[PDB]
Amino acid sequence: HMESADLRALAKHLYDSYIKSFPLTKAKARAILTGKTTDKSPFVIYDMNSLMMGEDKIKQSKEVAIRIFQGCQFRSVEAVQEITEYAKSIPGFVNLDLNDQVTLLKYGVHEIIYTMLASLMNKDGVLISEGQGFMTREFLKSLRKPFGDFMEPKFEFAVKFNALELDDSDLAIFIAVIILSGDRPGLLNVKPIEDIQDNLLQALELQLKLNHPESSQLFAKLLQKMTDLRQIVTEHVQLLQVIKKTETDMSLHPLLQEIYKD
Amino acid sequence: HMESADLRALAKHLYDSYIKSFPLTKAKARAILTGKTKSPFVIYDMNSLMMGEDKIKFKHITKEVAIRIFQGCQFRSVEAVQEITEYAKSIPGFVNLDLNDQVTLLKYGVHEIIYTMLASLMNKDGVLISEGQGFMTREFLKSLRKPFGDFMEPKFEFAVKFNALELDDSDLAIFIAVIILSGDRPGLLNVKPIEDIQDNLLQALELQLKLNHPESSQLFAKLLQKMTDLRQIVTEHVQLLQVIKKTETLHPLLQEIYK
Ligand SMILES: COc1ccc(COc2cc(C(=O)O)ccc2-c2nn(C(=O)c3c(Cl)cccc3C(F)(F)F)c3ccc(Cl)cc23)cc1
Ligand SMILES: COc1ccc(COc2cc(C(=O)O)ccc2-c2nn(C(=O)c3c(Cl)cccc3C(F)(F)F)c3ccc(Cl)cc23)cc1
Image (cartoon, rainbow over all chains, first blue to last red; front, side, top):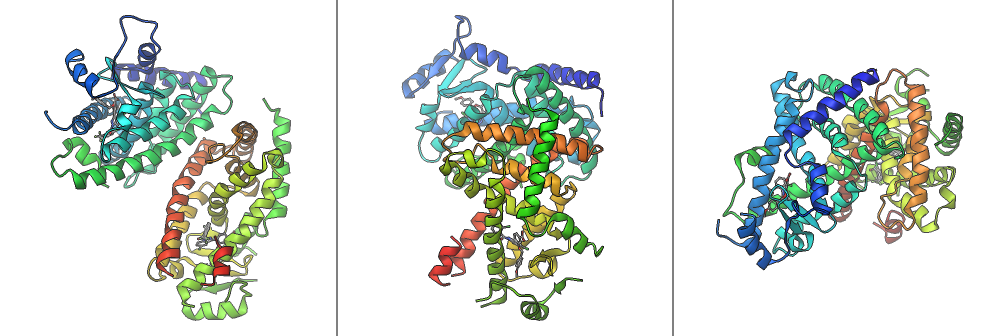
């Protein structure tokens, strides 16, 4: 459909914007996690005592599980802002009907947050504070009530997603494909969204073949991962609903508040 | 990896087996639904249902109307499970898998393939039954009482979207094989040969769709997306089965047949 020279151009464009939009890349996260460096090592939070020191080292007086939860939402709000900025760079997105732009972001940001959170994860924990900290999976799993169960499904996905060994240039196109989904509820003009997604899919297909030439059917394996993404988002909102019934003492950021309607 | 000549041979092998395994193909069903070919008996309300149960030889009649139709769906699904089980044995490599893994793949796969293949029998207005001798309207099914009406309509809602892809039987034979060989089913013992086979099936499906739908850009990717959806739809489906088989409280022996 599109000449390969044009598909390579689209990949370069999107990769360029991804670097401009997202401060902590997968390449940087892997350098921090795999060590070999003395200037990039994170402070590790694994228990109540190391958390207390972490607030002093890495530089709102409530229960611990609460404090950590609000820390996540703060970062999620930032991610939404970064993702919104990235989507405006996707060719054709800002030319869509304005209601559809909103609709695509509303149902797209969480699937992308989960995708990109995997970059910050290994089987034992997750980078935080722009990579200055690292909080262990075990510590997250041991938080009380429903909060302990919140964090773990992210990890089971990440371990599976990370086995695909995608780099940032692959992820930049995958993320674009997620945003331009014509099956979001309430879309007004499905067809121009599908046309954009077709080009992005072509670009993702060629990128994955060139960048992982010994990785057979990686394109198909990557698309199937959108199953896993859909299931965790559902688990996530369902757990939020429980919290929005036990903890009437707290609420969400207006941006998250509006995202989670319908 | 696989030579193109080998992928076509695999596509042909699967097509031939699919034609032998399934009584009513998509091509035959489309002929019936479009009137392009003895008209099927139409069930559109309570009175014609009663006549249809007499004229058509329903094998499942042993209660309330909405119940009876539900039991017919179950009867036909149990039939389909055996038809799919027979088809999977023709998939190159399947019978050499560990026997527990063969069972596991079928246990979690049949529901997705039944939904997929039910689309072949559907249009926006109803569904073929009894090997195409009957046709029950969408409207009559949607209007069934308590949860039964909302049970039937999601099948149609999927089918309308899936059918816009305009796959034919030779496309579907490979797609069905791909679903069966899913290496992420829980409880699998030896994932590697399952993913290896699926890798070859995926190669064959990609080539089939390019030759058979050369004007249909990224149809391969679009179909893979539908395999995703199927996962969520089956989950909603089974949950509703649990409710219907719990809120709508027959014989213990029939209960075991439909476990
Ligand atoms: C103590 O300090 C911190 C501690 C943890 C974090 C979380 O790390 C993330 C990083 C990014 C990043 O950097 O892109 C992005 C997300 C998180 C993160 N969100 N989240 C949530 O529950 C969440 C999500 Cl997904 C989406 C919307 C709303 C929410 C929330 F409202 F319900 F909260 C997580 C749950 C578990 C884990 Cl392990 C990570 C996340 C940040 C700082
Ligand atoms: C006299 O009444 C009828 C007799 C036969 C039919 C034909 O129905 C099918 C045919 C095939 C065929 O021929 O390939 C295949 C499927 C059905 C059919 N399954 N199904 C289900 O709920 C269902 C499904 Cl999807 C998957 C797994 C298990 C089940 C079940 F266990 F929960 F049942 C339906 C729901 C609605 C409709 Cl409209 C059709 C189906 C319809 C009505």
